[PDB]
Length: 75
Length: 89
Image 1 (cartoon, each protein chain N blue to C red):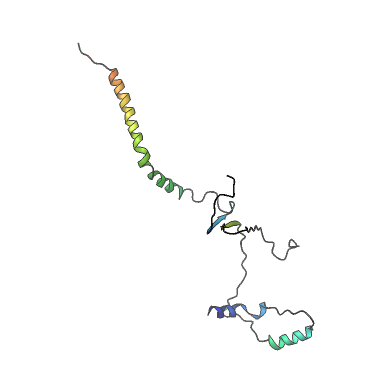
Image 2: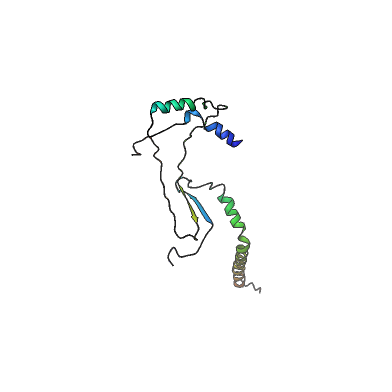
C-alpha cells in the first residue's frame, strides 16, 4: 500500500495556508483551557469511578492488615 | 443601475487610449480622434475616483480533489515582480 491507489474522491476542496503566516500559538490561553475542560468532562464519568474504588480498596487493605496485626487480650 | 454606475465610473476619457497601427497617418488619426472622441468624458461623478491599493501575495494552497478526470492539473506560483524593475527582464 503505497501512496496513490487509495480511493476515489470527487467533490472535495481543501484550503490551507502557509505555516509562516499564521502564528505559532493561536489563542492558546483562550481556547485550549476550555477545550481541555470539555475533554475532561467528557471522560471522567467513564474513567474516574473505578480508581476511587481502588483507593477505597487500598485504605481497607492497609487498615485491616494493621487490625489483624493488633491483638488485645486482657488477663 | 449598476451597469450604469460602472459605465459612468470607469469608461472615462483620461484612462482610455486610442491605439492604431498599419497603413495610416498620425495626422489622419489625430484628425479623426478630434472629430469623434472629443467631448466624450473627463469628469468623475461625485469625485469617486478608483485607485489601486497594493495587494498581498498570501501564499497558500487549494487542492480540488475530483478523481473522475483523466489528467491532473497543477500550478505553483511565487511573488510578483511588477512592471517597472529590470527584474522583469
